[PDB]
Length: 70
Length: 55
Image (cartoon, rainbow over all chains, first blue to last red; front, side):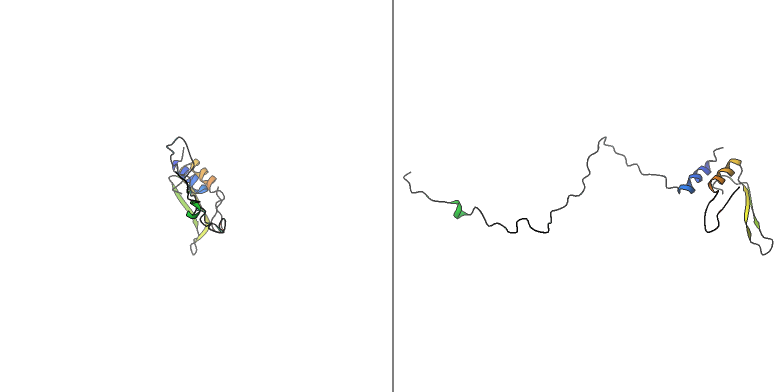
């Protein structure tokens, strides 16, 4: 005979009935990388230790006027 | 032992004097196969510091 009630109890005592896994169905036939975190650049030091002063100020932009006859 | 099948009848050993158990007993559930699978399961089963043996 099967002793059907016992076979449940058979696996019960030696394993502990935690035999059911769960699965999540992947409807997509493919698989790509999960959108896991991408953290933010918060350094210890700064990259060049000084904000550079303005390189292209106006007094540098205009180099000369012209005094010519056109 | 209901769990291992329908049990027919059970009986254990109690003292006839200040009645308490001498720590053994007997059983038949119905079947030979039920008996042997229960034995295979609980052959050397454990609990606090007795351990059941079965025949």
